[PDB]
Image: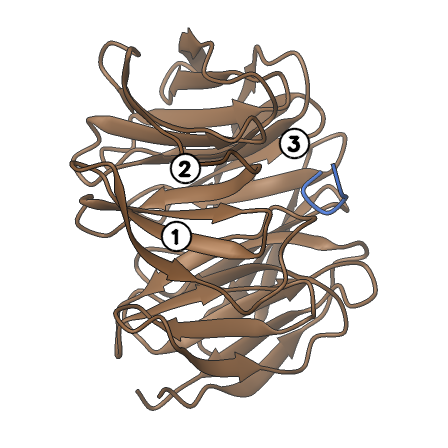
Amino acid sequence: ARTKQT
Amino acid sequence: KPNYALKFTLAGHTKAVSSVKFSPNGEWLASSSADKLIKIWGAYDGKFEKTISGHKLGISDVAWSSDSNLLVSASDDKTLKIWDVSSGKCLKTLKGHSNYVFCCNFNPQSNLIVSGSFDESVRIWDVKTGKCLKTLPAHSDPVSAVHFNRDGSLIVSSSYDGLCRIWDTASGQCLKTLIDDDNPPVSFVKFSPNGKYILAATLDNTLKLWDYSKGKCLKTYTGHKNEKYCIFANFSVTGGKWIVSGSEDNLVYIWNLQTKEIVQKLQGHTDVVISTACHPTENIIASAALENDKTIKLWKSDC
């Protein structure tokens, strides 16, 4: 999700 | 300068919080998390109201219907779900994206929901049937944000492909593409209150306010840290006219919209502030942080 760096 | 001071800290999520949003009628704050949950809190006193659950994986975004009765969430489980806030029930599950759903929003009429996914598309869904109406091949990398303008006729989307595009809602065809002299990943975008401007975040520690009609950059805001996460940005309009944003140095930054000068930095969170929201009528800011913090803070200013 947005909570992890992509 | 405003003088935001911490008034409440909301604990309850068990993993990093992903977004916070105040209901339009202003009585509630909704939060989404990678813990697969949505929580509702009292907007003025931070009172924990309820947990809404059902998604099978983490949630990246949650958004309110204009009448404050519904919520739509975007999850890594590849679906979006429409919820009735009062009952906590899932009314519809929107299926069709082929990868994580990242962002979502209701149009002003609240008859449509627009979504953005890692699958690089933007979809428009019928709220009442829960069916996908259009699938737009919007970008060539994950879609970081989607937002309708004030009369609902336009949708602005952003992507890691470095573009920000504006779409005609009724036809789904692209009206315009905005590109800087460069194309760093565009991590967030939204129309200004009147729909004339577009606030955009890029992963080079920069926020920019663009004139939609002219397609030109009017203001640039810097000083915070943003190179890794898709961090929301807001227009604060209840008191002084500011630009608000979280930051990777754990602070909430507040800039004067016209002068671009930083007027306040809110200290308190112990991890990246990934999301901020501004109350619709009171000078109140909600902020949320990642894993080492997992809490939501409510700040209030006299101006």
Colour chain B appears in: brown
Q: Which residue is mark 2?
A: B180
Q: Is residue B273 left or right of residue B168?
A: right
Q: Is residue B189 left or right of residue B46?
A: left
Callout 2 touching callout 1 (CB < 8 Å): yes
Q: Nearer the viewer, mark 3 or mark 2?
A: 2
Tag 2: Cα neighbours inside 10 Å, few (<14), some, or many (≥20)?
Answer: few
Q: Which residue is mark 1?
A: B208
The chain under label 1 reads B
- Say yes or no: labels 2 and 1 on the same chain: yes
Identity of the residue drawn at 44% across and 74% down: B254
Callout 3 touching callout 1 (CB < 8 Å): no
Identity of the residue drawn at 53% across and 43% down: B62
| Residue B77 sits in quarter | top right
In the drawing, what numbered circle is on residue B75?
3
| Residue B177 sits in quarter | top left
Seen as rendered, the residue at the extreme front is B181
